[PDB]
Image (cartoon, rainbow, N blue to C red; front, side, top):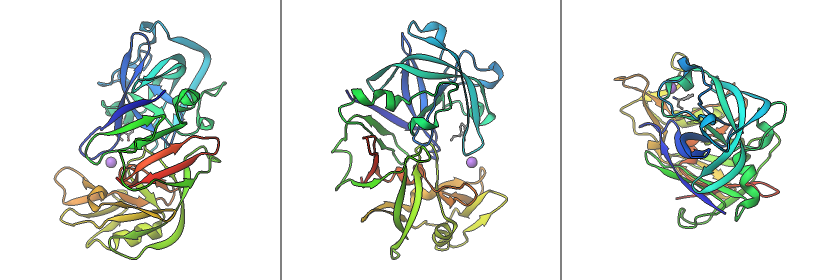
Length: 330
Ligand SMILES: CC[C@@H](N)c1ccccc1O
Ligand code: NA
């Protein structure tokens, strides 16, 4: 089997991407944030505290003929940005882009933190990191990918995120029309439950490539590119008037600037992030200070290749017995 679904930016900045997901019988379609950095599939629901729901579409298990309570199971998650949610668990039929899993754990939110409430465009998360990070207790649950895998034509999914445009998540096949050149594969460590890999270096603009190992995670659920402070300083030093602002919470730059590109290495291959991708616009409405898309990972404890980096590539998440990542230009 295979599946193919379009993923759409939630806003003009590509802060996140939403993908429609069918849950239950008859189908209830919810727009979920697919997250290669976490391992829970959780939704706004008929159980979510009413004051914490503001415009999201909810899953109502009582209207699904295939929903069953997973008795005794609870979940609670805390993300890198401080957001969180928690609740109880159903099993139900879940379909993505025509690929169906029966008996998927669908984590029903009883509580969501204010960042979730405030964002009416995200109806929940679909985690695509390793199932070792799933938070269901007392019986840990599998991701949608892990449950689909044995049915798939090839044990893979691909992320093809758009810049200010829709893109695609495919399951079970590699669309050879969706990228240019060849795919370069690189080793993955699963020891922290992430798609963790080592970039071979970077370049700023038309500058020389610096060979240096940068461990980090491929995270579709993080907006920005978080890299070591040395690398980030070297990037922003090439932008007139850029500075790190403790008041704003990262590097800002004059909105009048033209940003240089940023290149990262994948083995001997190179992925170029155009300068425009690194513009996250005014820090507040009408400001002439703009927020940068490359930020320091100091204090996060890991480097994160978030959407800024991933959207510049066609990315293969190879879930074979020995997982690997692939990157191609597009
Ligand atoms: C990434 C979109 C943003 N409005 C957001 C939405 C929900 C939870 C956290 C969070 O930062
Ligand atoms: Na923000």
